Image (cartoon, one colour):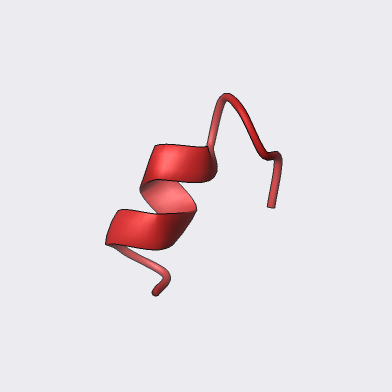
Length: 15
């Protein structure tokens, strides 16, 4: 995961 632009996305959706 891109730990900035997608960080929120990865945590929320992708666990």
